[PDB]
Length: 301
Length: 300
Ligand SMILES: O=C(O)c1ccc([N+](=O)[O-])cc1
Image (cartoon, rainbow over all chains, first blue to last red):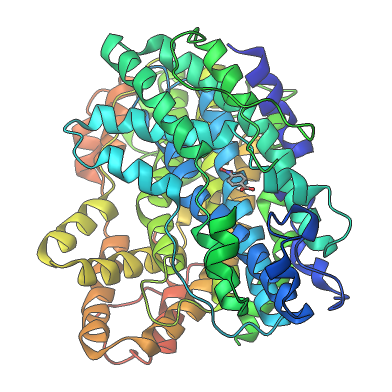
């Protein structure tokens, strides 16, 4: 079997966030209210006159809002997209998925996603308590998940829905959110915010390599119509993850009471790093077969 | 907020198997084939004439099979019974489950279960490789799970289906498998078999405490149709976890080639520790209400 997978499985205890920083809760021990929750430098409307026209506390509420929103989206992605793909592999629904090495690598990844959800949930709860955020609108469904559910809606056969769920999860795990990497490195914000994202990023880098190996091994064992289905779904999943939907920015801005929110939003890199998914496509021998224009690899990757 | 929940949440990093023994895979290192997989002492037919009349390799294969069978059932219970209950709580479907302290304790439990699944899956794979078992027959449906399906068939809408899943999960997590506790302490079997079960038991002791606190809080916020449904549900789950299913014994014997497997099973304590479940019952004030005869606490 895959030497990459063997390596990753053996390294998991030395690498995983759950092992090496289970005590993340205690990181709020000596809290400093004076330090921002989110970096202005990565806010797209940061230097817009209408955002600058606001009062300092209003800008701070937007930053806090964007931090909480980012954590909400991470949790929804894990729960709705990434973990269901991993679960399908463990359920043995694809030929070749009964392999002990695939099962070890993916179950380890499932333990990691559980802990990621734990860390991001803690981040929301601590922020909401300490910033005294009593109530906040529960709204927008992920653009990525909306696209998934629409693809699946009329699909007759379970075998094909399984492919779609696998591909959506694979793309999620190989296309790193710019906010994850940018937040991870940021020294201007709450240290627990850059720490949680640093931890998640370390695990996600491994998850991307795992997914590339597992997807190659399963595609190899698939029959032609399964292979055909995987190929069709790739560009559709890729486009869903390339899609910027700034409905969340609007809500945050309106929440903070910023005048001209619709104007600021209607007015608008933070592109994902698609490097991993490009490697995935290469390992499947699909280089020329996928109709997707891959963005350049970010400096931070 | 619950002082129990608080203490268990803050202790989790020191307690959790996932933190303490993430490198469980490496425990197979200097592997000694001479050490048994499973203790004859806790095998219910160990002293049966027809078992004793079988060859030494046949009896050692049964022990291997029962160890693998044990692990298979643990994984199935976690995946089909315990995790769904915990997920339901995190899904916020029940009033009062939005509580951050509840959410931390239960999410930590979910991390634990994913790692328990990992440990047990590893034990199966490493045993199957080292004992050279290339072939193993399909296992029967869990008795506990078959009974769950039955209740869910009888009880209709989404709203009742949530309550049943919750109770099934709660009973599973508060009634400790005799085999869990007896394997954990066994000094004669593969060190990593007693280690995995020692680790799982340490976590499960905490999970039982977590579940009693959570279910109590969720019971308080339920509407009258819901409480009625939960109360009617407790004894059925409890009976389900108390009923013995001999079908998995008949498989290990009929696989290892032991003649008269039917008579052995025909001729056939490993009773769960219901202590945690009894506490759950009193915490709900259903002491007089529940028609279930709790066995005396087992010695272990
Ligand atoms: O930081 C993020 O946005 C992020 C979201 C999801 C995943 N994930 O699918 O595990 C990782 C990072």
